[PDB]
Length: 358
Ligand SMILES: CCCCCCCC/C=C\CCCCCCCC(=O)OC[C@H](O)CO
Ligand SMILES: CCN(CC)C(=O)N[C@H]1C=C2c3cccc4[nH]cc(c34)C[C@H]2N(C)C1
Ligand SMILES: [Mg+2]
Image (tube, rainbow, N blue to C red; front, side, top):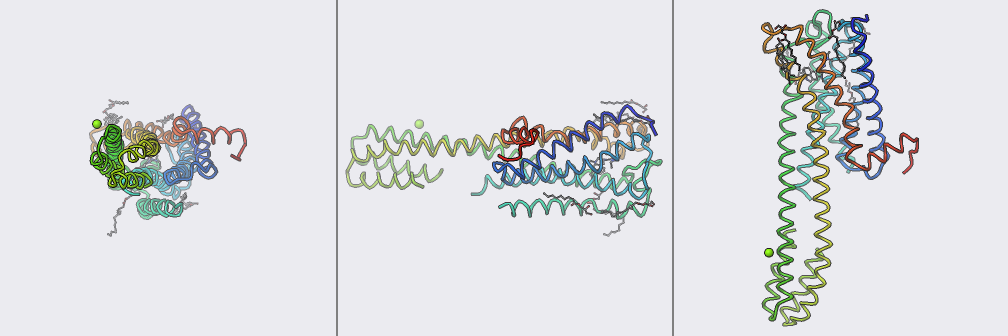
């Protein structure tokens, strides 16, 4: 005991910011009805994972730092504590991958129960991924102990576990994020194309002298609206006048079509800027998970590669540092939501003032 007493002051700060911030997230998705969507339902499940990592794993870790990385508890709790840490971390990364995938599929498409079934699937996948760690590690203390330190000692568990709980969900998540960004760039682009078509043909109709010019322009306007409804019917109403030779009537109907076009373009176009706003916040969450966990997972693989060549006491001392940089990620998602989403910031501000009604 008290082999390192300076380090555990800092780790208590990281434990408290984790518990309290993620309690504010869980409260905001439970209570604030502007946050009742499928992405925020996933962000709450991530927050429970971050909270249970802060309650269950992180105090036991600080306890080991206070005992000189020398396991202070009953010995069959070591494999359980490895299992909790690996379960919450597997759940977190496949949540971010499910968010990224479900939001990409939403931009190639037109219930809380449907979100909640998916969350349960991610958690039940994560329990089955993490399952060999107590099943094998409780039967053999050499898979979870290294010189009285509780740490995942089995090299095949580290390699299998580094890919199926960090690198293959990351790969799917970074591909789906890029494709999502490209889809939004295609949808902001196709809209601008439809705007130019509609605006150009309205100017054609306003200068038109013959029915044929008006009819052709309205046919091209109808197609643009169909590519992007009330507008289509209004265009068809102008088309019948144009087919009837009522040029002046069709021209007056077209100046009225303009107000409807402005409303629809700005709405579908407000909702493209909002999806790019939302994608940008999830990108910071995705980025901060990877960059803060990269020094732990790269070094953990390098321990297994240069097992004998490298200084196992330096590598072991760097992993003790780098696991807490990764634990610090559990404090950061609530801060990201505060900085970039008004609804979370307002929710957090009222919950701190013990005002729980909207
Ligand atoms: C097919 C029948 C074989 C049964 C007898 C085998 C005995 C060998 C020991 C362990 C196996 C581990 C199972 C690995 C299967 C995938 C587990 C996984 O996905 O990850 C492991 C875990 O995440 C770590 O971090
Ligand atoms: C139990 C706490 N201890 C002992 C000091 C740690 O070393 N914790 C780290 C272990 C991890 C690990 C190692 C190997 C394969 C893996 N697949 C998924 C993970 C993982 C999660 C990862 N967690 C987030 C940090
Ligand atoms: Mg033009």
